[PDB]
Length: 309
Length: 309
Ligand code: DMA
Ligand code: DMA
Ligand code: F3S
Ligand code: F3S
Image 1: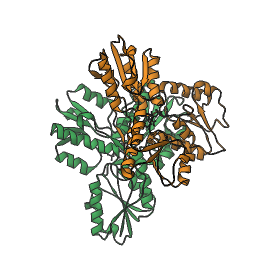
Image 2: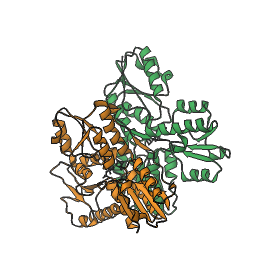
Image 3: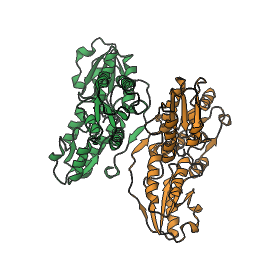
Image 4: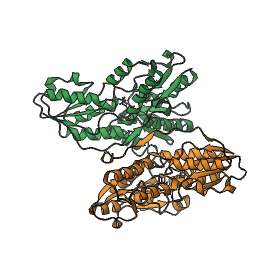
């Protein structure tokens, strides 16, 4: 059985920065360090940090006074940010710069009292944080997940309307939502294409290439990782059995039973060590040396705040 | 005399990467290493690299077969890229990712055969490279520098039009041109605001804050550096005497005599050592300890290609 590895795969710049922020905070201030929401959606990373003294909570009311709190890479609403500010807490923001970018556009629309539409998945922390940047009652902030949602949305004034998107969506599905938005609201303004980040776009391009060669695709990533789910979904849509797994232990023999070529990739929040263990398991199951496919080279790095070096 | 330092100032992520590409190529392959055009618009940087074995040329035809060629941070046209590709040369592209980003949009428009308008300064290498991404004869690629140029522009189809901008322009001036574009071509499409990079936006924001306290502003940068000139221009437009200088040696006593507060900043292509030397010179001219102003933190880094690390 041939083992192919998608390229690029794994850690993006926002995730590496976010994890480093927590690790450095722990090294500088020692345990415990509070983090609002899993720093990144990866069980291994979260479990490891917890073992190191990090405490993950969902609400600021779960954080003691005088404590150190870090916002996850997914970002937080202004309400959450203000609640933390009103509290006696030292705050470090690990929100990815590319999520913050969208936040600023929403804040701008809110200040102008102009309505905005966000394309994203309800319930996701990034959506909650981004929609949470809009506060002007005279305007409006709406969420749409599909063309159907666009088809039934009504706004106060479509002459002054803008849109933004979640950073980890399916490039193809989002394109369809945007087409619908422009057909429905011809005067709507937004980015050239979307707010989907480079890492998401690159990994989806990479898994598409992997899928046209592999019969089965394994995506290393946790169940609550949006970008990871989109990778598995993309492969499945291409007619390939694709599985989202946290570690090599989740691999079932039947999945690669008599398979001549299996492909492996990883979400933006999955550590390389997990991929290495998955490859080792596949090799125990008959796979040969892992072959990395040629791909788009990534060179972006986001540094931790000087205050945490 | 009080010395204030703008923040941020100096090296951006694109320049740091570009210089590192030339330095590492030299370290790995040794001299000579050929570079098309100045890697960055800074006399000191170019002179230093030349002293290290880099040979700056104007046309790829000046480069011998089997040699190593590097494209400057400003980018190159498709014609130049294809010329190098057909040659027996090892090519490393130091084009800044943020310039490449704009290149991609122009190529996209050319593919669709839709006309594009670039806001930029004629003669600049970045403009040459970006307009050089448009090839479709059925479309069109136009350059505009002012609102006036927009008023006089004639296009084939105003229904299918898009715009892009140079990365180092004046944020305020470009805003004026864009306002004119949308007023003239209501259906024109483009980015939310412009293609001015974070570094340019941040340095202009920083010099604005500096000029509010300083009576005189020294901008470290070469005469052919677009972003550097915009910093000096911004300070001068605020009513402060501004000087664009290559190094401490250019400082004239008369410029700062009796001056109570002098501010110092540097363009994206100027090394920090030059700023340190300028501060030293100002100190022997009566200046005190240099005081860094508080500013927007930058955390972006662009790694050199894996082959050159
Ligand atoms: C945009 C972002 C913060 C990505 C990090 O990956 P993740 O799996 O932790 O988050 P997501 O669920 O958005 O893919
Ligand atoms: C966009 C870019 C490559 C900036 C680097 O600075 P530079 O002085 O070398 O070039 P520019 O003339 O565009 O400011
Ligand atoms: S938005 Fe940021 S954290 Fe990762 S997947 Fe995208 S870079
Ligand atoms: S476009 Fe790139 S090289 Fe510097 S000034 Fe801007 S980052």
